[PDB]
Amino acid sequence: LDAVRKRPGMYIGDTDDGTGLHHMVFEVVDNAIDEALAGHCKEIIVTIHADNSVSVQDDGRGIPTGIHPEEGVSAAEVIMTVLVGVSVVNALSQKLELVIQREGKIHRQIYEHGVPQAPLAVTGETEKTGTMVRFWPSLETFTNVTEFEYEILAKRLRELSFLNSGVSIRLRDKRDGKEDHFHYE
Ligand SMILES: N#Cc1ccc(O)cc1F
């Protein structure tokens, strides 16, 4: 990830005018939609938290957890730490929390500035499947516009709901209780 850390704006977009900040969300949403499309229920939930982190969840199969035979870490960690892709989001997040529900098990992992704090670990059992990422954008990178703007997210998620017409997209703002549900049929 050092190439991204060296020139963040070249990977994510302008880091002073809010452009790059919102692009962080959109990169994560792309992966969540892909995951949701491979499942039965086909819903993603985007939440803006009161600490100005964002989470994206899907109810798909869960991203793969097995050890990548070539890299020697979990496949989820390969996705998060190898090179725009969610690895860029991770590199530019002061914290990122990953939760994967798959094959009867809950898996969790924490990153700080793209560095895993421990290996992906089984933490419990579950009947559900899906993936959730919550990220706190790094305030060492993102300046001036540091808070998410509901309308910027809503506009883009609406476009995505029409293109991905089988996918339900919920947007929730925990700062003021604002919510939308984009679903085309
Ligand atoms: N990477 C990734 C990713 C983030 C959120 C989600 O719901 C699914 C994903 F594959």
Image (cartoon, grey):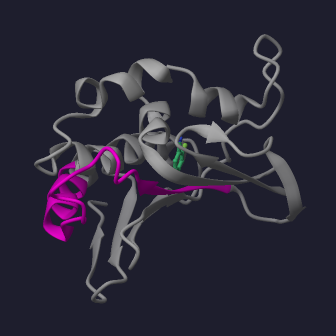
Say if residue 6 shows up in the picture: yes
Say above or below: 183 vs 173.
above
In this rendering, would 68 be left or right of 139? right
Say above or below: 88 vs 148.
above
Say if residue 104 shows up in the picture: no
Residues drawn in magenta:
130-159
Q: Quadrant of residue 70?
A: top right
Q: At x 30% / y 64%, what residue is drawn?
A: 183
Image quadrant occupied by the C terminus: bottom left
Q: Quadrant of residue 174?
A: bottom left
How many badges with numbers are in the image? 0
User: Considering depth in this image, is 152 or 148 the residue closer to the camera?
Assistant: 148
User: Considering depth in this image, is 120 or 116 the residue closer to the camera?
Assistant: 116
Q: Position of residue 105 (x, y in %)?
A: 85, 56
Q: At x 16% / y 51%, what residue is drawn?
A: 18
Q: Position of residue 61 (x, y in %)?
A: 67, 47
Q: Position of residue 28 (x, y in %)?
A: 42, 45
